[PDB]
Image (cartoon, rainbow over all chains, first blue to last red; front, side):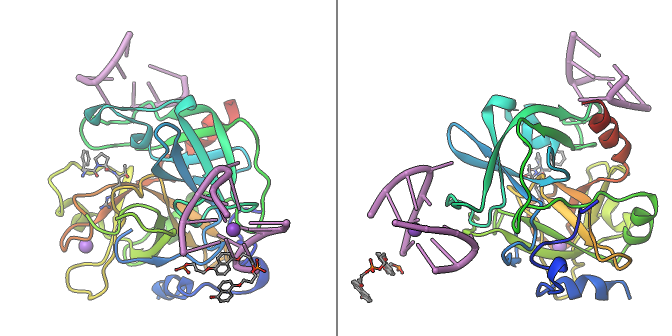
Length: 27
Length: 249
DNA sequence: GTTGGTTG
DNA sequence: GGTTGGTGGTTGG
Ligand SMILES: *[PH](O)(O)OCCCOc1cccc2c(OCCCOP(=O)(O)OCCCOc3cccc4c(O)cccc34)cccc12
Ligand SMILES: *C[C@@](*)(O)[C@H](CCCNC(N)=[NH2+])NC(=O)[C@@H]1CCCN1C(=O)[C@H](N)Cc1ccccc1
Ligand SMILES: [K+]
Ligand code: NA
């Protein structure tokens, strides 16, 4: 139930350089 | 990966590398789904047409890696397979249908900054996110051209509608497979290649900010060719088999 | 059915 | 140092 949250990313409120491309595609 | 870029540290902490023992060689990508279970493409382990048969003894699973070649001290963990589980209806003869396999590890892994499980989709997660035009993310250590990168590569590609998939190849498509990649007139490109098989095609849920594995790198014709699109095992369509096998063993 | 010949 | 301790190593520079 901890799956899919990255310790160095989501778990720390930081974003990787490209994940914005993914979310943006959903428009 | 073709036309991708270096993964940042811990950007894909479920990424797994399938390592042949003798000779020491990188075979394939895989992915971590629990502390005990790893997911990969069937063809990685079994492909008679190229004389490919690997079982438990032949293989190592390396987890938490970033550097392709170098051992990573106190970052990467190494497990041995207790039991492989190819999907019974895996069609190595014609079209790599149900190109999927599970592997239970002998010792469960400790999670860390670099090793962390991905989520597998449910009905609606699949339904909403798996759609023509939505981009996903492919990672792996495979070939940079129709290769040998030093560090885990990454690329994001748009899911493509069936008609375009089917009309791109004379190989018979099924609904256990989807295709992804930029069309010829889109200026952006990129693809998985030979070596990336078993690696996940992941999507971030805008609903709960979680990563779901929608796909497994399966096949394609060359790499990064205008008019051609890489193909991925449809992970959800095979979700029941996955749960089935986990429950039992 | 770990399952709708490529396999026993 | 590093994604990690103390001349390579389960390993490059
Ligand atoms: P690629 O193309 O970068 O090739 C590698 C070349 C760089 O080599 C090294 C860079 C950094 C560190 C080391 C190294 O470190 C282990 C010991 C840590 O330091 P120390 O306290 O043991 O060293 C004492 C001081 C020695 O410093 C130098 C010695 C010789 C030359 C130079 C120099 O030109 C600039 C600065 C310092 C020194 C071990 C081996 C290689 C490298
Ligand atoms: C095993 C994996 O490393 C690799 C991934 C290829 C990714 N392709 C692209 N460009 N998206 N898969 C393969 O090499 C597969 C397994 C066997 C051969 N193969 C192919 O992709 C063939 N080129 C095409 C093919 C042959 C037989 C049946 C279906 C497809
Ligand atoms: K070192
Ligand atoms: Na293409």
